[PDB]
Length: 107
Length: 108
Ligand code: HEC
Ligand code: HEC
Image (cartoon, rainbow over all chains, first blue to last red; front, top):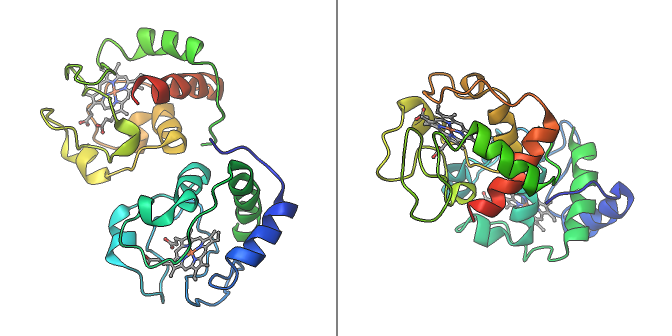
């Protein structure tokens, strides 16, 4: 399960693996992927001004640290049909660190 | 609600004293007052066949996990208004953590 880690390590992971497609700040733009401000406690597929797959929408995930960790392990396994082109983060430590960063960066 | 892994030993005792009267956990275990909970952490609410749910539980369509289960068990009728699960709730985070640690193992 998710355990608080290092947002410092997390930020580097996010920057090298996610930032290309996602911004995190309030009012930051949608790009290849949606802006993630407020993602934790929001349902999947709900950010306005972004065109999602029906798959992402229908999943009805209420994003939290634990289901995010499962998603990021292997996105297409968690949401078959998703257009997020990301293989996954296999190490629990990396997901813990990334998610620690993301919670703080998107709140 | 935050979840932290706890004691399944303590969780099992919580399950026996607070849940077992209405629920089974094992694969193929019977529906009773409440539905069998095998596989609950891989599906949405209201989806076990052979059990008659409220519309409220079905409509909620919650994708159960540790965090939202913890929120639900704090106060079920608040989380799913109109649910017929007659359970007041587990007010202490430690108890929820322990129970959910047990449930993850017992229902897998
Ligand atoms: C493009 C090459 C991306 C990279 C790299 C990552 N993500 Fe992504 N993500 C992308 C798209 C196109 C989408 C929408 C998918 C769909 O099927 O519609 C997403 C979606 C997410 C989500 C869910 C957002 C929501 O429901 O509002 C999350 C939480 C997310 N992505 C996170 C994320 C992280 C943390 C990344 C690096 C580890 C990452 N993504 C990479 C496109 C791309
Ligand atoms: C009867 C007196 C119950 C007790 C005690 C507990 N539960 Fe229950 N639960 C009960 C019913 C009748 C229902 C169906 C509710 C409806 O509105 O249709 C439920 C439902 C659940 C669920 C959702 C299951 C699903 O969506 O498939 C869960 C996860 C659940 N119950 C768990 C649970 C736990 C952990 C309990 C003790 C702490 C517990 N319940 C007590 C009836 C009763």
